[PDB]
Image (tube, rainbow, N blue to C red):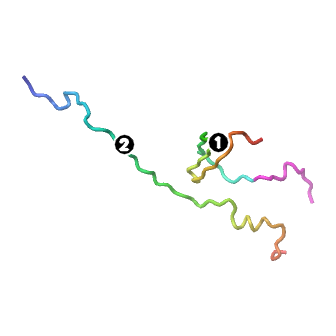
């Protein structure tokens, strides 16, 4: 078989959704990401994920 | 002396204002994290295909 480098060949996370308008709000020491296109809301901590 | 239109005299409001707007109609689309085919494909070997 043809050999390819490991790092640019595999992905442990896969792109699922693209959101044009995902409103971000800061509330209760958390970030709320709300999308009306998919009617979906996520809650995250205020700190970035490296 | 003369006649006057109703608009000629400034009016003070004797009504208390109450503003209500309706809830907007929303549409929920079919959205799944993983489909049936992706979950089936997750397996490394399939006995039937092999």
Task: Name the residue located 62 percent from the left edge and 48 percent from the top edge.
Answer: A19
Q: Position of residue A41 (x, y in %)?
A: 61, 50
Q: Please, which chain is the residue tagged with disc 1 on?
A: A
Task: Name the residue located 59 percent from the left edge and 61 percent from the top edge.
Answer: B30
Would you call the spot at circle 2 few (<14 residues within 10 Å), some (14-19), or many (20 or more)? few
Chain part drawn in magenta: A1-13
Per the image, the residue denoted by label 2 is B19
Main structural element of the magenta stretch: helix, strand or loop? loop
Task: Name the residue located 44 percent from the left edge and 51 percent from the top edge.
Answer: B23
- Which-is-in-front pick, marks 2 and 1? 1
| Residue A12 shown in magenta | yes
Between residue A39 and residue A6, name the one nearer to us: A39
Q: Please, which chain is the residue tagged with disc 2 on?
A: B
Per the image, the residue denoted by label 1 is A30
| Residue A5 shown in magenta | yes
Count of numbered circles on the image: 2
């Amino acid at each position: 078989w043809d050999w390819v480098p490991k790092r640019p060949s595999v992905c442990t996370m896969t792109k699922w959704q693209e959101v044009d308008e995902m409103l971000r709000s800061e509330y209760g020491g958390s970030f709320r990401f709300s999308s009306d296109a998919i009617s979906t809301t996520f809650t995250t901590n205020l700190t970035e994920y490296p | 002396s003369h006649q006057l239109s109703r608009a000629d005299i400034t009016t003070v409001s004797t009504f208390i204002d109450l503003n209500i707007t309706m809830l907007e109609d929303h549409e929920f689309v079919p959205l799944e994290v993983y489909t049936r085919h992706e979950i089936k494909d997750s397996g490394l070997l399939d006995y039937t295909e092999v």
